[PDB]
Image 1 (spheres, chains in turn yellow, brown, purple, green):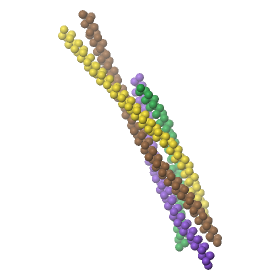
Image 2 (spheres, helix red, strand yellow):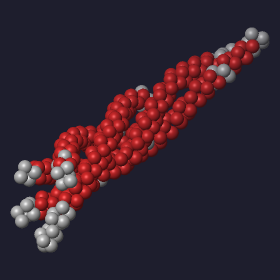
Image 3 (cartoon, one colour):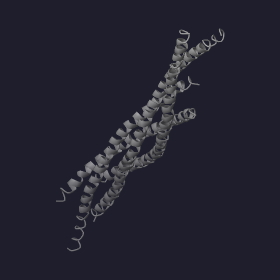
Image 4 (tube, chains in turn purple, blue, green, orange):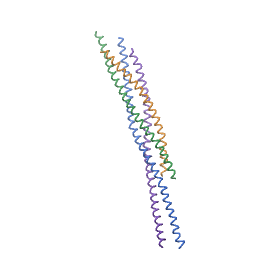
Amino acid sequence: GSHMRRLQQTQAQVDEVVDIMRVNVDKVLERDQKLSELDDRADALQAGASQFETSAAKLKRKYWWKNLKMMIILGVICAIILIIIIVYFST
Amino acid sequence: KQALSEIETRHSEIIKLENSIRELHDMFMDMAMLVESQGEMIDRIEYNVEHAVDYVERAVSDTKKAVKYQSKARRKKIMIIICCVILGIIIASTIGGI
Amino acid sequence: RNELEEMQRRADQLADESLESTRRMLQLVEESKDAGIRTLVMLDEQGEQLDRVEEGMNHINQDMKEAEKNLKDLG
Amino acid sequence: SHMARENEMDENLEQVSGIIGNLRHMALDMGNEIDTQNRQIDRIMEKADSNKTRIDEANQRAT
């Protein structure tokens, strides 16, 4: 009687659920392909970055020394003019 | 006889519902699986990014220190080139005065 | 009555499998509920991690533009 | 008793029908969030490809 109604509707409900969970699975699969692929760039950008961190790390050193040079070569030149001076102050 | 064909049709569907609920049970365990399984696949995309974010964070700060010493070298280099031409006319006067 | 007795035993026999399955179903649901709640609580935590991750790409794409100038001032 | 048996299974079956009212809900909320994240992931990749081309562009500007 009134329990043969529960069956009618309590079923279509589940139908609805699984029908939905069907399309949900097809989304969790696009998630796979979109993710596993992004992960291929997570590496390929931790490597594009850590290889530019090398180029950059060095671009600092090499740069740096040319400032030391030009304060050593301003030291000898500030000393050569100093001695080229002790020689026209003397005779 | 008539109430034995109604328990036969009610039971007949209580299993048609139980066999259908198991299918939905699996749909939810087949979900806590693929999601949580991809949960290991995300932490690696976070780990890789938080490092790749940090690599760029330093990699740019160095490009800055790496333009400072240029004007500082350039100065210290032409300050030399100043005291160079200076030395050439300080020695071109011991040739213009024997 | 021997034929009218082996017909109410199967009648009360289908009420043991309908009562046993009403329990086996009841549990298949709660575990689908619980195994569902966790699926959700995770989509949230994951959901947050993906947000830091997006900030990262804008934070990055912003700092790359910064270096694209300090590479310019240098030939 | 078959009067407290049919009164029990038609009682713990009340819940069965109930929780599947929950499952129905969870189903959607979960379903939509995903399509939000998928849309997002799609976004992040387009911004990633503009970043691996600006790194490779600038990393061949080191030589």
